[PDB]
Image 1 (cartoon, one colour):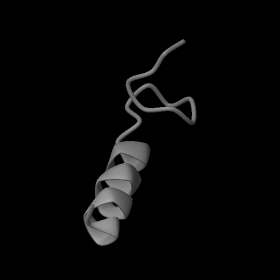
Image 2 (cartoon, rainbow, N blue to C red):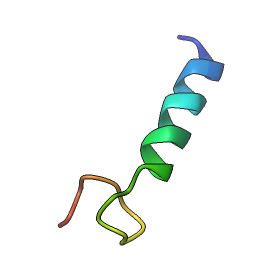
Image 3 (cartoon, rainbow, N blue to C red):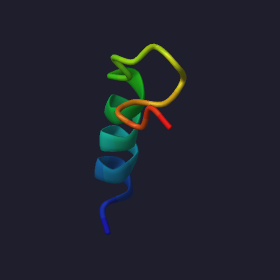
Length: 28
């Protein structure tokens, strides 16, 4: 699998937390 893509999407997902609690859309 594409490491750059995985890292990138993971980074983006990490950054776009929205909930403001370290995790993204994982409020649990």
